[PDB]
Image 1 (spheres, rainbow, N blue to C red):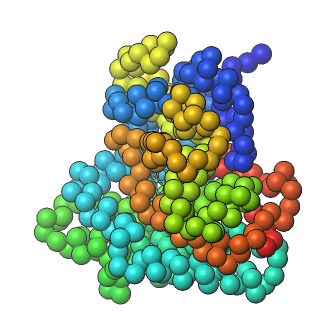
Image 2 (cartoon, rainbow, N blue to C red):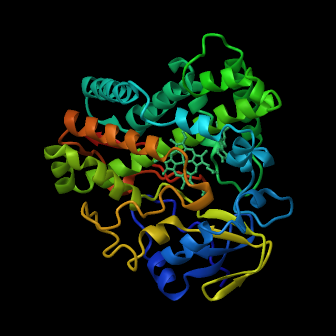
Amino acid sequence: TVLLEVPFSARGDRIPDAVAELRTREPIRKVRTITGAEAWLVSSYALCTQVLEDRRFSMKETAAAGAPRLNALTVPPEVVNNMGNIADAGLRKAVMKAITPKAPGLEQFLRDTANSLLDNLITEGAPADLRNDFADPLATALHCKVLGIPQEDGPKLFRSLSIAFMSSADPIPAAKINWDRDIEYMAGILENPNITTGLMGELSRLRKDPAYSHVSDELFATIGVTFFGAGVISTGSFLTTALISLIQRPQLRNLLHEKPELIPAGVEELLRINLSFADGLPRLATADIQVGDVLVRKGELVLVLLEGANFDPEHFPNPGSIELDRPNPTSHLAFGRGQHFCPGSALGRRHAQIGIEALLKKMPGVDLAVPIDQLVWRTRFQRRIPERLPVLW
Ligand code: HEM
Ligand SMILES: Oc1ccc(Nc2cc(-c3ccc(O)cc3)n[nH]2)cc1
C-alpha cells in the first residue's frame, strides 16, 4: 500500500472517523498531496496552534520555486504574501477599517438583501437552491457594498471563483485569464470617479495621497481582486455548509428561531464544526523545528488540519455536538491563528448571523428537499461546497 493521501473526503457534512484515529495515534503524520509531494499533516489542537503561532513555519515561503506543494499556484507568487505586502505599504489599518461590519447601514443592507432573496425564493416556490439563489448572491452583494463597486458587476466577478479557488495538481490556464481580466477591471475602478465608498473608494484616495506615492498600482488592484475573491468564496461557502448543519438539527433550528439572541453563539459553534476548508493550511518550515514526535526539517511542507484542531476532544469535549454554552467558544481555528489570522472574521460572522436570522424568520420550517447523500460535493477545490442545496419549507 501507498502513503496516505490528502485530502480525505470532499464531503462537508460529516468528518471522516479516520481524522479521530489519526489524531490519537499520530497527531503529526507524513502524507502525500495531489502534486505528489510529501507533507506533514498536523491534526491536534496543541500541534496546530504551535505550527500556526510559529512564524518559522512560513506561509510566504510556500511560494518558493522547487518547494513541496500542496497544490498549484493560482496567483502570482508574490500575491501569496498578500497581507505582508499590504502591511509593508502602510495600508493594513486602512484595509481592516474598511472591511468591518461596523460601517453605518451595512448590517441593514445585509438584512434587506437577505429578505429580498428569500422573498424571490418563496414566490418561485419550493424547491429552492439555497447556495446559488441565497448564500452566494448574499456574499457577493455584501462584498460589492464593502468594496464600493456596483452591484451589477458582482455576478461576472463571482463566476471566476469556481476556477480561481481550485486545488489543482497543475497550473490552470483559465485561472490566469480570469486573474488578468479581474485585475484590469479593478484597475479601472481605481480610475473611476464614481467609486468613492468602500474599500476601493478608500484605496483610490490613498493612491493619490503623497504618503503612498511609491506604492505600486498593481498592489492597489490586487487588494480589490484578492479581497473580493477570498471574502465571497469564504462567506458563501461557510454559510452554505452552516445551513446544512442547522437543517440537519431541527431542535437547534427551532431554538434559534424562538430565541434569536442565541444566533451569535450558534454561529460560533457552526464555525467550530465547519468543514468549509478543504485542505490543511500550508506552511513551509524555514528551520529544523520539533513538532510532537517529529523533527520537521527545513524546506518541508506542513499542513494544518483545521477540523483536526476544531474536533479535538482534548480541547472541545464532545466535539461533534453543538453546545451553545462552552467555556472556550471562540478558541477554535475556523479563522486561523497567529500572524495570518483572518482579517475579515468580524464581517464573516455578521454575514452568517444575518443570513441565518433572516432564513429562520422567512422559512422557519426549512428542510432538505433531497436526501443528504444526493448533494454533489465539489472536488479538487479549496472549499467544500455542494453544487446545489435544494430545500423546501
Ligand atoms: C466565514 C468566513 C471566513 C472564514 C471561515 C475564513 C477563514 C480564513 C482562514 C482560516 C484564514 C487563515 C489562512 C492561513 O492562516 O493560512 C483566512 C485568511 C484570510 N482571509 Fe478569511 N475567512 C472568512 C472570511 C473572510 C472575509 C469576509 C475576507 C475579506 C473580505 C477574508 C479575507 C482573508 C484574507 C485576505 C486572508 C489572508 C490573511 C493573511 O494572509 O494574513 N476572509 N481566512
Ligand atoms: O476575479 C478573481 C477573483 C479571485 C481570484 N483568485 C484569487 C486568489 C486570491 C487570494 C486571496 C488572498 C490570498 O492571501 C491569496 C490569494 N484571491 N483571489 C482571481 C480572479
